[PDB]
Image (cartoon, coloured by chain):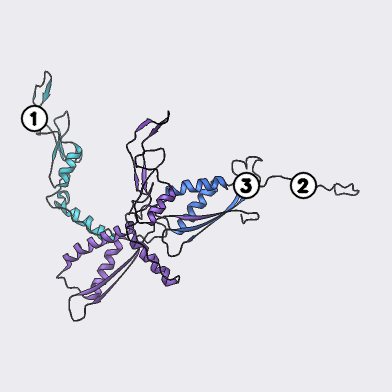
Chain colours: A cyan, B purple, C blue
Amino acid sequence: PNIIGPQSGGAVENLPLHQYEAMGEIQTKIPTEVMLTERREFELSEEGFIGLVFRKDSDNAAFFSANSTQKPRFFGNTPEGKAAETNYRLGTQLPYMFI
Amino acid sequence: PNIIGPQSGGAVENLPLHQYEAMGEIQTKIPTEVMLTERREFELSEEGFIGLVFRKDSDNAAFFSANSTQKPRFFGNTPEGKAAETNYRLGTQLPYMFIMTRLAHYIKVLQREQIGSWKEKSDLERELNHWLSQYISDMDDPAPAVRSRRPLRAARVVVEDVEGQPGWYRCSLQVRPHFKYMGASFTLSLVGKLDK
Amino acid sequence: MTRLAHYIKVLQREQIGSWKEKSDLERELNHWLSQYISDMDDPAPAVRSRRPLRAARVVVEDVEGQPGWYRCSLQVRPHFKYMGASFTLSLVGKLDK
């Protein structure tokens, strides 16, 4: 279950780095194609993707969450309906399915 | 339903302004052609128009009410007659019709999903009751404008059978929405020996 | 009463469109009017000035066959101005000290 956090154990440490000339300055090729923002990561998470985000200015990346492909179901906003949603959402996430 | 008030959410903010010379002074072209008075707004409301009034000396306008074109019907001044008038007037106002419109849309969709299921008459009454409760706020005093997400206060459902047509039902849905504050009369009076 | 009438007209227009039931008006109107009430045993003289009222009562009813409309009654008991008095002077023996 411990696979979804910078501290929890979803952190990927010791990524390759590559400093090269930019527009007269120096920059490193990002270990991942892009430097994913928190908003864009969250968007990907909503669409059931597992985005490995890069920690800016380091050689560390992290998996903020491991949602499966399955899309959560919505239920009526009642005590029972919200309990149904809670139970179904637990099913949709890999950290709990591994258990 | 929250579309009929300066604070409720019928306020139109950030209107264009245009200061220009007057008779030696300066004035701004009113964002609306005129500066509608309370009396003139009320007159327009009586004639089933939706008048966007301008807040004097600002760039804000408001929709005090959203009455439809329909003219209210008058009934005999009895307990039943006044109840008829109350019910008919609710129908004439858009802030309440929007509630019924969304209810109609939810029923059409959700009910098509249920076609083919093993439903007896009382099965529909049980499920329909549990469903409608989703949008009901029947507490002593729900947080003001929170009533907003739960527009209904009470609701009643009855289901009967379409005789000589097994599997078909006749359903009646009646609802009591929370009321919008839309006017009041005040009587002021000085008094001695008033109870403290 | 004139200033009260002016405050009611203004402040009430701001409230139009809000989810108000009959008892909602009684609750809020009561809390509002208390703003100008000085119902103490003995408020500092001419301080009563900023709070002209001593007591006030509000009742709200419904305009039957017109949902959303209310009939409100506001009655107030202002502090009294000293505006005349009659005096009876009398010499007396064996008066209680």
Look at mark 2 in the image and give the residue it sits on. C85
Q: Residue at position x 38%, y 50% from top? A: B64
Q: Is residue B180 left or right of residue C56?
A: left
Residue B49 placement (x, y as % from top left)? 34, 53
**Residue B42 versus residue A32: which sits nearer the camera?**
B42
**Residue B19 versus residue A7: which sits nearer the camera?**
B19
Query: Could you tell me if the residues under marks 1 and 2 are in contact, i.e. CB atoms within 8 Å?
Result: no
Toward the top, the furthest residue is A24
Can residue A3 be seen from the camera position used here?
A: no
Picture disc at residue C40:
3
Toward the right, the furthest residue is C93
Task: Count how many numbered circles sit on residues in the image.
Answer: 3
Q: Residue at position x 62%, y 56% from top? A: B194
Tell us which disc is closer to us: 1 or 2.
2
Can residue B106 be seen from the camera position used here?
A: yes
Q: Is residue C50 left or right of residue B68?
A: right
Q: Residues within 10 Å of mark 1 (few under 14, many from 20)?
A: few
The three-letter amino acid code for the residue at tag 2 is: Ala
Disc 3 is placed on an element classified as: loop
Cα–Cα span, label 3 and label 1:
78 Å
Look at mark 1 in the image and give the residue it sits on. A16
Cα–Cα span, label 3 and label 2:
25 Å
Disc 2 is placed on an element classified as: loop
Picture disc at residue C5:
none
Corner quadrant of residue B23: top left
Where is B113 relative to B54, above or below? below
Tell us which disc is closer to us: 3 or 2.
2
Disc 1 is placed on an element classified as: loop
Corner quadrant of residue C49: top right
Q: Which chain carries label 3?
A: C
Toward the front, the furthest residue is B23
Q: Residue at position x 26%, y 57% from top? A: A82
